[PDB]
Length: 373
Length: 65
Length: 191
Image (cartoon, rainbow over all chains, first blue to last red; front, side, top):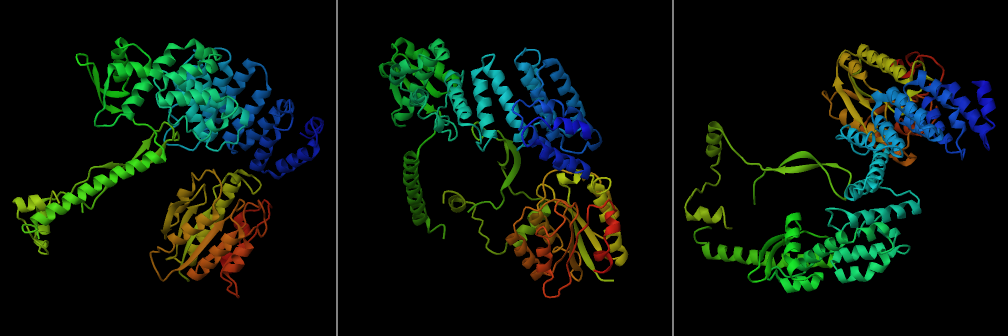
């Protein structure tokens, strides 16, 4: 120990003081303070090569300590593996540390997530998918484990970014952002995440909300000037404005995935336009016509029936189609996010409703007071 | 003006934007029933204000109003 | 002879992994509370003692019971985890020994602080004055030696027994690998 630490001391600035502190903590047998110090230690060396030698020291610690938080043990092991640059030894080390912890739980999940992340660059269908499935049940009635949840959701988001499941990636990215409730992450990182989440929402198979994505108070606020065309097209999708979409085509036409997926985006915006029209129209009329839908969605009258049927099948709107009269009777459109002016309008409508209720209650009471006293 | 009992059952709630799954209380229908002895005792004790009038009078007060 | 309802506040925090104090601070404190419970029972057969942990938030394990076997048995499986919440733990103990089985008994709290307390001075002194009004004595053990000093604890105890109250106590133990039961001699006998 003594000579090992003395020789390793000459690895970074100001190291001798921290090495002396570590020696003092070990001698005093303060396992947890030593653990905090070791966790903070790895951050110093930019290359982090000394940690590749402190493997023996941490092994010696954990051998007869075996009480320190195995979660922290897995964190330091993760740093060591990150330093290590050969996949096979990385996998073996992760497996052995997983066996070592096992009983702790909440750290086995972290080790599995590390294995998945390491193997994601090389092969997916053999390990990544079944590992994502495997880490699903120990997450049971045990919330607020952000320490593992963030890593797990990042791994899942990366996997779904691969393969090409935009909807699942959207769900996982939203989950990761929610799990890391505090931001404390680089502005560049959160801005890239915002861009990816917006693209996933646009390209998703069955995600028509664009009402909470727009007001996500953590990401969209950070793409407000750099790449504003994403926010602009998201607003166009939310408002169901096919004309604004077509005009903005120039901005997003440079995006390769969006350019490749043009029909899907067009059908999504057309369905959103139908929803917006149904919501805008008052409840008492709510009876749209084929020519109006065609004009609004920029499609010929013939395709109106198929568009409305797709909407009904997916579940955006409820109603019927009367080809003889060339009309659609919409009876229910999906709920959407409303602003404070619309909330106040709802309040006024409630006021009218309550006034009517009170009027009838007073009428009945006054007229039947004789029988009910 | 209503029943005095409200029943709740603890359930895990999964969101779409609220994200973290919290343990929330979910409503369950609650009603008041009684055995024969309990019914007899309650009816005996109910000599505070007794007004049966099962006819249109009660069908107007217990409901409508 | 004196009736006393004493609630023990044990510290199952992550700093109890430390082996500085004999075979792990957890086992040292186990033996310490063993001797304290036995001492209270021997002092009075009717005396009743309970157990509370000072884990992430708090947890009551055994309310006042004249027997000690259940308390000791529950003490097992007290594996360490999380931080220590001194104010919340002491408030919960205060409630528990306010809901006594016998109101003629006295009220006491034996606390094993083996980890730093993150409560400011103002909150701790406010708790001290409230407990003084409610007539509670707080025997505090400065176990663990994470600060091994008046880590906002001597102020607590002095505020409690101010004006020659000589009711509370603060026994500070050095990291010397000597049994905590061997170290404790003030509260057990000269209470």
